[PDB]
Image (cartoon, rainbow, N blue to C red):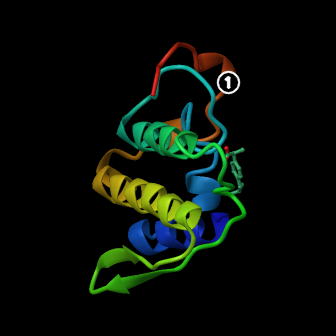
Amino acid sequence: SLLEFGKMILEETGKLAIPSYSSYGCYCGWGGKGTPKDATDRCCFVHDCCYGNLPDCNPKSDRYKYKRVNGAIVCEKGTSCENRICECDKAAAICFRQNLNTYSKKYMLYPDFLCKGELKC
Ligand SMILES: CC(C)Cc1ccc([C@H](C)C(=O)O)cc1
């Protein structure tokens, strides 16, 4: 769920999910279209695609458990939707950490009309 996702992001980046990653680019947070603006926005796009592979799960409200083993994120065993949701989020958080150096404030609150395009998962 969002709860877990938000806390993973903070632990990983030292940034709060809202609002550093909830209105960024074309996909972070409220996506649907266009070309992702940078590496961080691409993390969000792949994250959307990851969720997109679980039609019958509810990644926003279904809660899972994970633990840190030294720095590593380890998803604990829950239902099959939970395991798979956690793997999607874990990847997004690492992707965020990896591109933290190009994170740009120019992309916060990015306007909808500039998200245009077509990009298939
Ligand atoms: C963090 C808080 C603002 C929740 C939030 C943000 C964006 C979305 C979109 C609709 C999505 O997840 O597809 C859902 C929930």
Q: Is residue 76 visible?
A: yes
Q: Quadrant of the N terminus?
A: bottom right
**Residue type (three-letter) at the residue carrying disc 1:** Asp
Residue visible at 68% across and 66% down in the picture:
62
- The crowd level at tag 1 (other Cα within 10 Å; few <14, some 14-19, many 20+) is some
Residue 21, above or below 78: above
Residue ID for mark 1: 112
Q: Is residue 16 visible?
A: no
Residue 46: image x %, image y %?
44, 40
Q: Quadrant of residue 32?
A: top right
Residue 46, above or below 59: above
Q: Nearer the viewer, residue 5 or 121?
A: 121
Left/right of residue 107 with respect to residue 37 in the rendered view: right
Instruction: Give the total of numbered labels.
Output: 1
Residue 3: image x %, image y %?
65, 71
Residue 83: image x %, image y %?
49, 66
Residue visible at 66% across and 27% down in the picture:
111
Residue 116: image x %, image y %?
57, 14
Left/right of residue 111 with respect to residue 36 in the rendered view: right
Q: Quadrant of the C terminus?
A: top left
Mark 1 vs ligand 1: CB below 8 Å:
no
Residue visible at 50% across and 38% down in the picture:
49
Residue visible at 29% across and 76% down in the picture:
72
Left/right of residue 109 with respect to residue 82 in the rendered view: right
Q: Nearer the viewer, residue 90 or 79?
A: 79
Local SS, label 1: helix
Q: Nearer the viewer, residue 37 or 81?
A: 81
